Length: 49
Length: 49
Image 1 (spheres, each protein chain N blue to C red):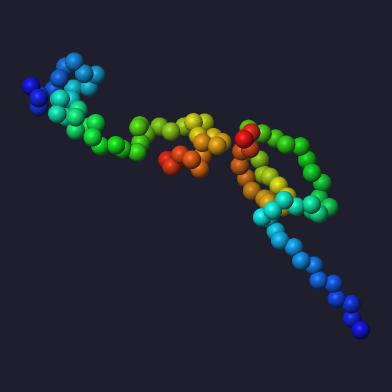
Image 2 (cartoon, one colour):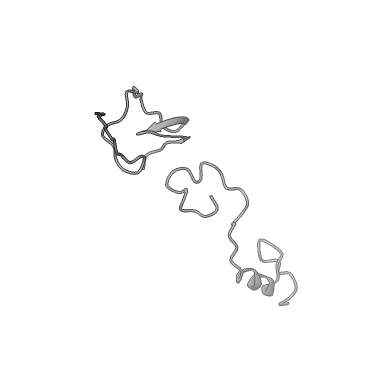
């Protein structure tokens, strides 16, 4: 016998609740910063909406 | 008088020339669009930016 565990999920389309072990930091605004929002990486300037 | 320049205008365009200029709508009112002019929600809503 073999035990098989199959894990299903969707990525970067909906709000998430699990996440990984990475540790978060503070939010910097009005500056050029690399960001990682719920797994989504990129570069830009963050401003209030 | 309708095709010669008119000195009463800020430019030196004729009446007919001004009428001609007012009937073509360009997309760039000037050529200096600053970065701070469209920063935030203005982007993805202004076609030029």
